[PDB]
Length: 522
Ligand SMILES: O=C(CO)N[C@H]1[C@H]([C@@H](O)[C@H](O)CO)OC(C(=O)O)=C[C@@H]1O
View 1 (cartoon, rainbow, N blue to C red):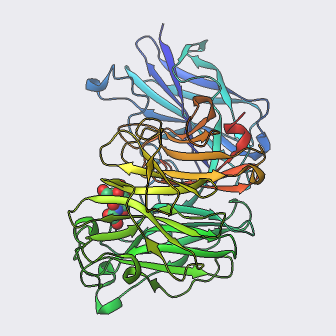
View 2 (cartoon, rainbow, N blue to C red; view 1 turned 45 degrees about the vertical axis):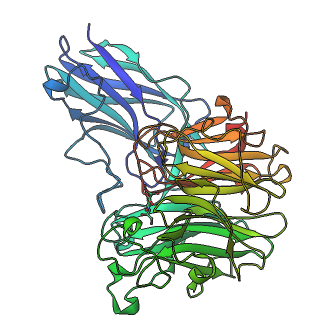
View 3 (cartoon, rainbow, N blue to C red; view 1 turned 90 degrees about the horizontal axis):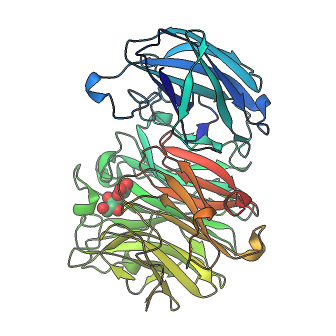
């Protein structure tokens, strides 16, 4: 007989999307003629009232040289890059064979599809209602598949007990006339307001130098809805150079918890033609030679933003090629000191990560010594009072480098977890510390997020540690995005019980997801 192979997806279901890939079906029809229907059963706890529709699409066949490669689709069904074409399945790739609006817990999708004498691809689409809850979870099973009016044998290659989580596409390719959005940062203000910052890359997805601003999405309802985009940092035709030679990017955001003043730091590149700032910034101090470290602050819960504050003169050694913040977020230590992770290419052209701190509420800043050589992007958290843990992208590859300091970066101690506990593909990673009194578990925890792999940027994962970063137990992890993406992410606590994550996913340039703390630590 012919067997219908089923692969359930593990990717965010965007609430605003008209389509979301839920299942993929492959059928090599050696003895099959017609695929009549597919029967689907949603889980007992699923709220069907939040589901707008369920659809069955046919996507044709496969190239004969690709038979036996165990592919479940011939092409990407829903684009995350085509401006204005990221909300619905591409009609040229997928034929809508059936649709059920306002479905019941048991859904029958009739297809009546004449099968190609060979490989046939189908997939199931799930469309949520615009008002769907961020925390409700969707589970479903394929109960039966009818082929030639008889029950077809099924073999499911994906695992059981998959939990599909929804998310909000805070930024899609093309929004507000910008080709792409990258490099997320995410914080929660003292008033519970969510602030997410990112590169707005108008012309394309290339790094600096280019036409880039720092955009900000503000949410006052826990990430359900986001306010119109703001631009805390934009330099336009500064110095009478074109905007594409005045980009600002790689933002990092922090909240001064003592005052609720919000700070955003970024790297403004001036000149440099159309080349990458990583090898186009040079020693010196002024805009005409080296990238400038600029700040903007908000004293009204992120609604309005000040003019840029250039602190390059305070902290940059003139012999460095490039000084910039570590993208993502900063912190406020228990004693009130503000800390931003930073990275600089030194006089030998080697990058090193470290921290930059202010004891006077952000008026003056300081850098002492690097934590480790040949490291770049890093995130910092106060694991225990007075002890700063820096988690660093390591160009040696394969795993994160972790170090700690007790004197604000004058001296560093290599952590036991360094270069062993947390694998990476040399990407950016998020690290936050949540203190016992500020979370529902009444335990000090560390939350870490990154592509859980050594090659490629996929399987974006949040990991939790209860012993200050010594151990990251497998049962304390949630895999949110199996698809391929740009890999950058940033974490925050929405509330004492829920984590928020803003990251570059396979379904949207800026994707927001909410994960219950008890979901990770059960
Ligand atoms: O060029 C700059 C400096 O502004 N930043 C890049 C960064 C590199 O700096 C990398 O960390 C060193 O190779 O890479 C990525 C990325 O998504 O992989 C994004 C940043 O935009």
